Image (cartoon, coloured by chain):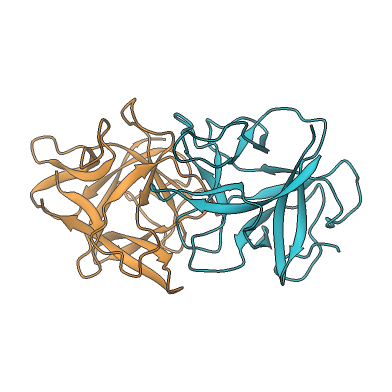
Chain colours: A orange, B cyan
Amino acid sequence: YTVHDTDGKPVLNNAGQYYILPAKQGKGGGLGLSNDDDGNCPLTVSQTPIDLPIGLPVRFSSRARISHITTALSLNIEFTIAPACAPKPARWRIFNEQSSEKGYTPVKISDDFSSAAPFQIKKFEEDYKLVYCSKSESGERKCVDLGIKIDNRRLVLKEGDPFKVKFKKVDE
Amino acid sequence: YTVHDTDGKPVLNNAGQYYILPAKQGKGGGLGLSNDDDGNCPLTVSQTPIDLPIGLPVRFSSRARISHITTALSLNIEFTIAPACAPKPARWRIFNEQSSEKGYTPVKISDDFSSAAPFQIKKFEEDYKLVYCSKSRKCVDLGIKIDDEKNRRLVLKEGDPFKVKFKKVDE
């Protein structure tokens, strides 16, 4: 499946800017950055509060020799607008020393740069979900749904409970 | 010995692209870049903490312009894809400092010129290792040191070479 934005247009590969918005009416807005145990810089991918429903734009990047993204691609995801304190690129990652169990680890931004592209977009009813695919210390490949932890509500690995998302195009 | 990739085919000299992968799985992914005291840009050659059989693509280049990489060749190694902030070329070279507390001598990327090609690939068990040969020349195994921190940095580590294999990037 080609991933479509809220205007029905294919989502670009390695170009343009998109908000990741909740697909369902809930207690927060689009994904942004907050400071969750990060020190001097907000590095944690989090829902914005409902009074500021727009977070930060992202760019989706795949090795795939195509101009648009499908639900088949391995992706990296980076915020295209980020605080000046933050690493470049502001690339999404999880911090877990190849743990066999990966759930409720928050998605953070990091410098770490490779062609390993652990995120994928999957269909979820009328809209989409995000998943994170990797192997553990045990060798097993798992793709785990990304969901919301309520505790700015954090984007975390959450196998039973995907955060339903849609994609709003900012710019090309 | 000619160096062979994961398919069994000789590694190309001066052409083609490879991932440098751990021969052992479960201990992180292929070699790419991380920020180890590098400021705003990941400059330090490190295993990706994502356990996937993928790294950042590397090109092997030697002044001797034969078709294949052997264990006798003096080599430059550079990442062919790097972050926007990285030096171009993203050429691998040994950093001239050990961190005061963390210690070890990491491989970093730099656009610095060298008269000498410092790397070699040598056989190691059933697969291979990377060694760094520094002209004042003496060759030292490159191994992985995990910091606190959990960056899996490629560093000088004579006893303890990081066993690697080479996956061709067309696939």
- Which is more toward the observer, A105 or A162? A105
- Which is more toward the observer, B63 or A133? B63
At 47% across and 33% down in the image, what residue appears? B100
Counting every numbered tag in the picture gives 0
Left or right, residue B94 beside residue A157: right
At 82% across and 51% down in the image, what residue appears? B13
- Residue B86 can be seen in this image: yes
Q: Where is residue A86 in the image (x, y as percent from the top left)?
A: 35, 32
Quadrant housing residue B136: top right
A100 up-or-down from B48: above or below = below
| Screen quadrant of the C terminus of chain B | bottom right
- Residue A65 can be seen in this image: no
- Which is more toward the observer, B143 or A83? B143
Q: Where is residue B74 in the image (x, y as percent from the top left)?
A: 83, 46
B38 up-or-down from A48: above or below = above
A165 up-or-down from A87: above or below = below
Left or right, residue A40 beside residue B40: left
At 80% across and 62% down in the image, what residue appears? B3
Left or right, residue A39 beside residue B113: left
Q: Position of residue B96 (x, y in %)?
A: 62, 31
| Screen quadrant of the N terminus of chain B | bottom right
- Which is more toward the observer, B124 or B33? B124
Quadrant housing residue A72: bottom left
Quadrant housing residue B161: bottom right
Q: Position of residue A135 (x, y in %)?
A: 43, 68
Left or right, residue B62 beside residue A136: right
At 79% across and 67% down in the image, what residue appears? B9
